[PDB]
Image (tube, coloured by chain):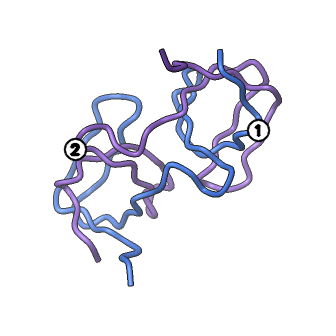
Chain colours: A blue, B purple
Amino acid sequence: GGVTTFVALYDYVASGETDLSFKKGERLQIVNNTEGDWWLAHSLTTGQTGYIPSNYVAPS
Amino acid sequence: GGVTTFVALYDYVASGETDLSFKKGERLQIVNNTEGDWWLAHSLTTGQTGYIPSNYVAPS
């Protein structure tokens, strides 16, 4: 059965606003683009990232 | 060429820690699983989400 969790091998310090910092030994999930009808999105105004309902958006 | 940016149609208030809040009219990117060797991850310890170098992790 597929793995549920990954562990960090090293410390990582983020340089941008889309990447994630973490400490060696930290426990992390690798996540999917989509969760049902929810898509992963990155807010250009608040710089944060997360899933959103795909029916709440339209192309520019 | 493909769309670069989406616009919010309504306000959304997040309920969990994997979902993203945004206001109507916010400009958002829908993001890809991977960017090169980098995968999207969700930190169970800090609750934050972001890209990480895939060579910095191992399965549990």
- The image position of residue B56, as x and y in percent, is 19, 55
Q: Which residue is mark 2?
A: B37
Horizontal relation, residue A37 to residue A14: left or right? right
Q: Which residue is mark 1?
A: A55
Relative vertical location of residue A43 with respect to residue A31 in this rendering, above or below: above
Relative vertical location of residue A25 with respect to residue B1 in this rendering, above or below: below
- Indicate the quadrant where residue B8 lies: top right
- The image position of residue B21, as x and y in percent, is 69, 38
Horizontal relation, residue A48 to residue B60: left or right? right
Subunit under mark 1: A
- Indicate the quadrant where residue B6 lies: top right
- Residue at image point 38% right, 63% down: A28
- Residue at image point 55% right, 19% down: B3
Q: Circle 2 — which element? A: loop
Give the number of the disc on residue B51.
Answer: none
| Number of numbered callouts drawn | 2
- The image position of residue A46, as x and y in percent, is 58, 26
The three-letter code of the residue at mark 1 reads Asn
Q: Quadrant of the C terminus of chain A?
A: top right
In this view, the residue in front, B20 or B37, is B37
**Which residue is at the far bottom?**
A1
Q: Circle 1 — which element? A: helix
